[PDB]
Length: 177
Image 1: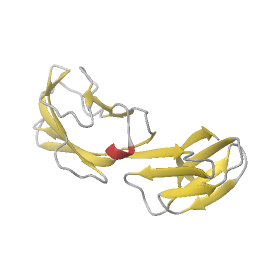
Image 2: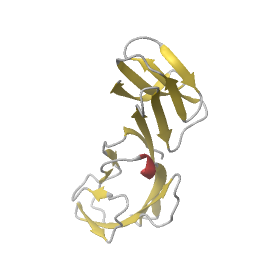
Image 3: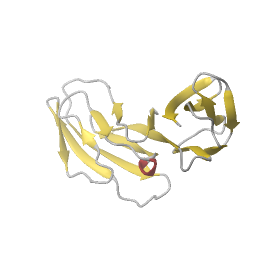
């Protein structure tokens, strides 16, 4: 089921749904819940006929983009902490309602003044997930088990910011301070 896409702001998230591509025709719908402003209405309606995907009136916020053919890739295109959350991609009567869960977690690293270095993430994170601000190739300076960690008066250099679950680093992002 589930699929998670980890991205730094300003990047593209692209999900790929690669299931049982026979001669199928579908009606498909994707609806999204953006994490802090859960203003319901995000969706895209599309249809499949002969391997050509098509969109029946979609939404515009975020601008979901669908692949005009198989394989059915949905791409949210210039990610932002404000679009992180998750949604389900319902597929239809292929034979029944086939479904997929989809998520997007977003990281934002900033140097707000020069006392501050910040790293914040938004979206669906496990609680065995911690944020880490490190110097480019050195060791973790801060490793807090929160969603926004901060570092006081960072030494000039490449800092890196990482999201890890267990010994698994889900993602990272660098900044030159």
